[PDB]
Amino acid sequence: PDPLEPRREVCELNPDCDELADHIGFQEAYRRFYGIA
Amino acid sequence: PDPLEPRREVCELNPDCDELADHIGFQEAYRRFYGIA
Ligand SMILES: [Ca+2]
Ligand SMILES: [Ca+2]
Ligand SMILES: [Ca+2]
Ligand SMILES: [Ca+2]
Ligand SMILES: [Ca+2]
Image (cartoon, rainbow over all chains, first blue to last red; front, side, top):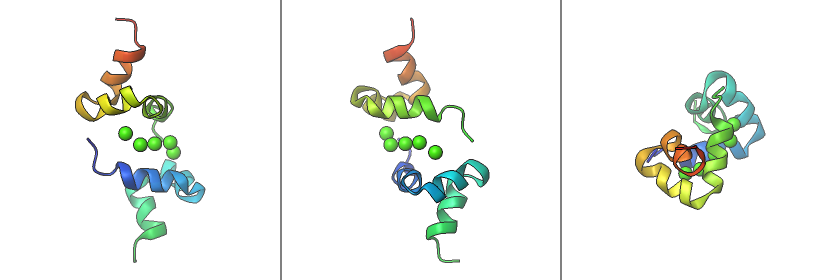
């Protein structure tokens, strides 16, 4: 199982993160909207 | 963007495919419930 699925679902839920994910990826997009720095 | 996202969503929707996906993967699980052979 993929440990990142929970975060991937969170991002999909956020249109802005979802859309962005298609360009720079999910892990980098998640960080952009939720990471600190 | 990942071209497989549509199929991944289909599988997640199917509990049986979802569960199975965690063990042998999504592409092999999808094939198991929807592929022909
Ligand atoms: Ca999921
Ligand atoms: Ca999903
Ligand atoms: Ca998406
Ligand atoms: Ca999706
Ligand atoms: Ca899943």
